[PDB]
Image (tube, grey):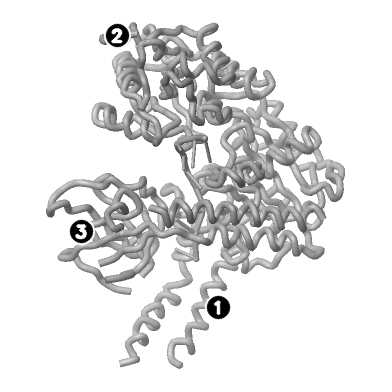
Amino acid sequence: AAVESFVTKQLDLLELERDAEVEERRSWLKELQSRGVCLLKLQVSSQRTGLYGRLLVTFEPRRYGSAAALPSNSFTSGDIVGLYDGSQLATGILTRVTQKSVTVAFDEQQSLDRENSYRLLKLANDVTYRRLKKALIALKKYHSGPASSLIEVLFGRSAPSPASEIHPLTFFNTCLDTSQKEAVLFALSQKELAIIHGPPGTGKTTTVVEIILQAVKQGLKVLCCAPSNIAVDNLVERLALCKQRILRLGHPARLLESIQQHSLDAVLARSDSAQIVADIRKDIDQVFVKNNEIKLLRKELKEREEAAMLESLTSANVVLATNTGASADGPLKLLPESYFDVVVIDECAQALEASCWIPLLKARKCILAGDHKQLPPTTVSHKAALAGLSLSLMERLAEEYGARVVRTLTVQYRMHQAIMRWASDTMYLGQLTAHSSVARHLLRDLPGVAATEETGVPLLLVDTAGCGLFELQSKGNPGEVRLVSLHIQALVDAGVPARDIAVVSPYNLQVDLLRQSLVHRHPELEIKSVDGFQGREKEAVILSFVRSNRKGEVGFLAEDRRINVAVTRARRHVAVICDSRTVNNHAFLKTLVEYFTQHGEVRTAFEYLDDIVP
RNA sequence: AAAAAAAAA
């Protein structure tokens, strides 16, 4: 069918990816590394247990035995690492990374001492690809189970079965607006597929939660997935507010801290498993004797553990995991197939479609939510990107079916209408609407915050042109750093706390840049890329487009959705700092600066900076 | 061409 060609082409697009990633891996011989994908002169600096009965050790670099340190390749939280003294000393996972620390959670096996020197290696992992391969296959080789119907629908085979016409709804959330209502109504009344298209600020998660509550009222069992841990946990922390009985699939690493309590790991540590661990010590006391043994009784952990987690999985109404966390080799394997009734994928338009097929083969209905007019899933292979990996299951369907399967939230509760309209008129067909409560709010309306030229204006653009604030293989721009700084200080002086402000540029260079010249004078001020700031919001957001050159080159500021995302992070105030001259060679980017100048209060670097040779 | 994130026993 369409599947046994989809799956066959999709595996292709997939190997193009793995390969394009094993390229920029095996390419960049033991110094070029620490830049980088490696940490050396690591001294051990703390040892404890935690999370949950693991070995949490902390490290810090030791130049000539003292500073500093760390230049790490972000070496971000949740990364799998090596650890060397010889060769492979163990394996563990990354809890946090400071520019002084890095802490790693070891799953135990032995110590390990202060009076040594260590190395730490970011390892690569084939699991995400392995499981994506395994998904697609199963989709290909699907008999006649429950997902069968839904499959046909997501692939043209057959059309959408009619409405299940749920008896009208007593809503838990009464302050719900009408778009959200037709949405919720419609999702529960489908039968194979409902798509919640939720633009920035429309309360898409208020809407999904409401859906899930109804589902549990009808006595339905739910799998709730998303591509990232951050997004799952969004839902996990909202479900938990509504008292719902919920389980979140480990590893707790990895997991929002406010919520460890809900991971399969914590539940399992609330017994009954003072017994299973009572003998965890057994097995460790017979690798000692020594001087068929363990096998004899490791059959006991199998049943015991798999007994408890089967129980816990059963006693929850909503089970939550990452798309790839719902792998048929994860805890979901203890459930008979036919266990879940619906599967919600939040942030679907932001995830490889092949992942979605992991959680998707487990229900016979699914709700998809997200905003395909913001960032698509990331692709390392340009070639796959053109071939359509960067296409989301949600987008594809949205393009195909339209209002036959999509319901779209329209009142938004974040942005002042000025900001609101750009994105609206620009990316969402001129249909967004401010809630009568956000449409006129500015920073001067905040408490402690004085009225001011800035704190009193929703939009603002300070121009690089033509003061020759040129750039300089990511992209920085000293002229812009400098500028934000001042506007930053204009905001913090007018009252605005830094905790309520964020600075966002598209390039990682401008970021470290911005950070270096900012972190110390404003510790609680978030500085991050646009891709590292999705879903977030702030009272005031300072953008930095960075690109200024005579050549007219915008880089990837051309990717429309990125820009959209960026502008929509602001509630009461977005100040864009770009170069009029260069930025204008891209239509979208132009009608933006055009907007900022029609209904905005604009300025030119001139008003801000002393040295001026045009 | 582009320089951007995920995920993970």
Of A138 and A489, the residue lying toward us: A138
Q: Residue A43 carries which label?
A: 3
Q: Nearer the viewer, mark 1 or mark 2?
A: 2
- Horizontal and vertical percent position of residue A131: 59, 61
Does residue A209 appear anywhere in the picture? no
| C-alpha span from label 3 to label 1 | 40 Å
* Labels 3 and 1 within one chain: yes
Mark 3–mark 2 distance (CA, rounded to whole Å) = 49 Å
* Among the two numbered marks 3 and 1 on one chain, the one whose residue lies closer to the N terminus: 3
**Quarter where residue A541 is shown:** top left
The one of A597 and A50 positioned closer to us in this rendering = A597
Crowd around label 2: few <14 · some 14–19 · many ≥20 (10 Å): few
* Residue A528 coordinates in the image, percent (x, y): 40, 34
Q: What residue type is disc 3 on?
A: Gln
Q: Is residue A345 visible?
A: yes
Q: What residue type is labelled 1?
A: Glu
Q: Which amino acid does label 2 sit on?
A: Ile
Q: Tell me if A21 is positioned left or right of A388 in this view.
A: left
The residue drawn where x is 39% and y is 36% is A473
SS state under label 1: helix
* Subunit that carries the residue with mark 1: A
Residue at horizontal 75 percent and vertical 64 percent from the top: A141
Mark 3 or mark 2: whose residue is earlier in sequence: 3
Task: Name above or below for residue A367 compared with residue A5.
Answer: above
Q: Mark 2 points at which residue?
A: A612
Determine the residue positioned at 45% across, 12% down.
A460
Of the numbered discs in the image, which one, if any, rests on residue A489?
A: none
